[PDB]
Length: 118
Image (cartoon, rainbow, N blue to C red; front, top):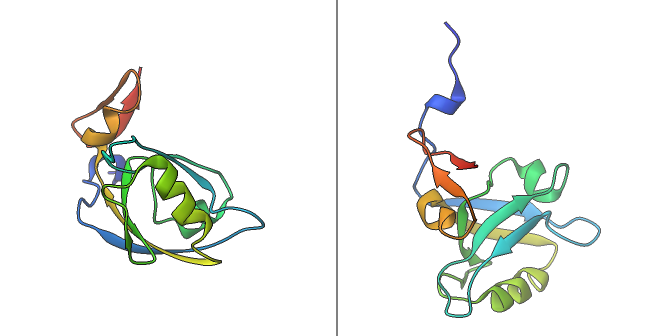
């Protein structure tokens, strides 16, 4: 009888998320490349602003920050944008585990669309 969340699909459409800056940061890390192959959330800090929003996850691609398109930005550019985004940060994110799993070693996507690492 239990209805497990892990068995229902994770939405794949883009979402708007508003993050309120902590004492320093937004409470997540990103990965990316110099060629701008995408900016992805790789880590969310427990208890940090991103976590407290409850609307972001590992494997999300950051499409824009405060309207600035980051789809083809390098890690460096994206990190700069996030730092200068102010205390109220509006993010457009889209869940893309397949793309992301090519960044993280020994990682793959299961049938439920979750990212698993061996």
